[PDB]
Amino acid sequence: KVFGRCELAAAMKRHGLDNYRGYSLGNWVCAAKFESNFNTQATNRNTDGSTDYGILQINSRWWCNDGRTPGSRNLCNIPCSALLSSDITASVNCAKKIVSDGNGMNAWVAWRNRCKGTDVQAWIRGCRL
Ligand SMILES: O=S(=O)(O)c1cc2c(O)c(c1)Cc1cc(S(=O)(=O)O)cc(c1O)Cc1cc(S(=O)(=O)O)cc(c1O)Cc1cc(S(=O)(=O)O)cc(c1O)C2
Ligand SMILES: O=S(=O)(O)c1cc2c(O)c(c1)Cc1cc(S(=O)(=O)O)cc(c1O)Cc1cc(S(=O)(=O)O)cc(c1O)Cc1cc(S(=O)(=O)O)cc(c1O)C2
């Protein structure tokens, strides 16, 4: 499923992402956009054998288990297919763990190139809140 902007911001807020470890809500919305275009089914392969999964493009090298990334860890203790679900709960919970561990959000490449140090609030303006 593809979220709209405001629908995603809203769900992210309900999951307590707003200002989580210092990152205002537009940050998580912005990162979702440039990682997956708001698509819960997004997946992308990496050259090391790992795959990024879901709305926040969470990597199987470190964070989840997809049974085909040899020698990988599963630090969120979660199957990667759970990161592909229509309900974003697992993605959110895994995203919290990544950030709190942590490298903040700098871990997300697209967030670092398109969101960090810009007007991330534009991503939430005009939404019901
Ligand atoms: O997209 S919207 O923010 O406009 C929206 C508002 C409400 C909605 O019921 C829905 C969307 C439909 C809907 C969407 C989703 S999601 O897109 O997958 O996030 C989930 C649900 C849902 O009804 C189920 C649901 C989950 C939660 S959560 O455990 O906190 O994530 C809370 C609620 C849910 O219905 C209650 C709820 C809260 C809120 S509020 O944003 O907290 O005011 C609005 C609406 C609600 O139904 C009222
Ligand atoms: O990822 S975080 O947003 O939590 C973060 C915040 C600060 C940080 O200092 C860093 C990360 C570490 C860091 C990372 C990087 S990068 O991974 O290569 O993108 C670069 C730097 C850095 O300190 C160096 C740096 C770059 C820039 S830029 O011109 O915008 O690219 C600005 C700064 C830097 O220190 C200053 C700065 C800005 C910001 S702001 O969020 O843009 O206001 C937060 C922090 C800053 O130190 C305070």
Image (cartoon, rainbow, N blue to C red):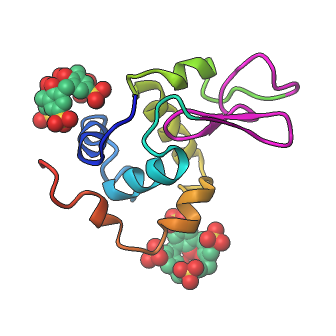
Q: Nearer the viewer, residue 83 or 74?
A: 83
Q: Main secondary structure of the magenta part?
A: loop
What residue appears at the point 12 percent right and 49 percent down from the top-left corner? 129
Percent position of residue 27, x then y: 40, 58
Magenta stretch encompasses residue 110 = no
- The quarter in which the N terminus is drawn is top left
Is residue 78 among what the camera can see? no
Any magenta on residue 45?
yes
The residue at 53%/19% (across/down) is 82
Task: Please identify the quarter of the rendering in which residue 121 is found.
Answer: bottom left
Residue stretch rendered in magenta on the structure? 43-71
Report the side of 86 relative to 100 (left or right): left
Q: Is residue 72 left or right of residue 37?
A: right
* Residue 86 visible in this rendered orientation of the protein: yes
Residue drawn 35% across the image and 72% down it: 119
Quadrant in the picture for residue 53: top right
Judge whether 123 appears above or below 63 on screen: below
At x 40%, y 26%, the residue is 89
Would you place residue 29 above or below residue 61 in this image?
below
- Ligand 2 sits in which quadrant? bottom right
Q: Is residue 87 left or right of residue 96?
A: left
Total labels: the figure holds 0
Q: Nearer the viewer, residue 121 or 105?
A: 121
Q: Is residue 86 above or below residue 122?
A: above
* Residue 81 spot, x, y in % from top left: 59, 18
**Quadrant position of residue 42:** top right
Point out residue 114 in the picture as x, y percentages from the top left corner: 52, 66
Query: Looking at the image, which residue sits at the far left?
Result: 128
- Residue 102 x, y percent position in the rendering: 59, 50
